[PDB]
Amino acid sequence: AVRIGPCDQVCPRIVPERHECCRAHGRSGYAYCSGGGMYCN
């Protein structure tokens, strides 16, 4: 699990946008937002 660029910005967005960030950045999918940035699977 790692952090994506806009994932922190699209974290508070809807549901399809949250999974779209990780999937669009070559990541497994949306996992959770901790500390000060969103983290993908």
Image (cartoon, grey):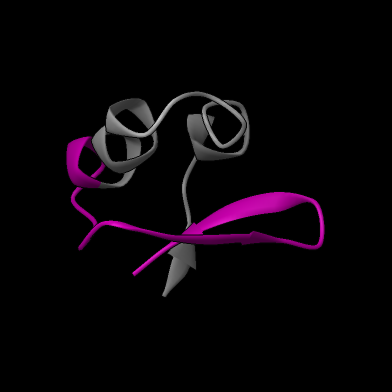
Could you tell me residue 39's position as x and y percent?
A: 52, 60
Residue at the outermost bottom position: 1
Residue at image coords 19%, 45%: 23
Which quadrant is the C terminus positioned in? bottom left
Q: Is residue 19 left or right of residue 36?
A: left
Asked where in the image residue 27 lies, by quadrant, the reply is: bottom left
At horizontal 50% and vertical 38% (from top left) the residue drawn is 7
x then y, percent, for residue 28: 20, 63
Magenta region: 23-41
The N terminus - image quarter: bottom left
> 40 above or below 16?
below
Task: Identify the image quadrant of residue 21.
Answer: top left
Residue 13 at x, y = what percent? Answer: 52, 24
Going by the picture, which residue comes out furthest to the front?
Answer: 15
* Magenta span contains residue 34: yes
Which quarter of the figure has residue 35? bottom right
Q: How many numbered dots are placed on residues in this image?
A: 0
Residue at 25% in and 33% down = 20
Camera-side residue of 15 and 18: 15
Q: Is 3 located above or below residue 12 in the figure?
A: below
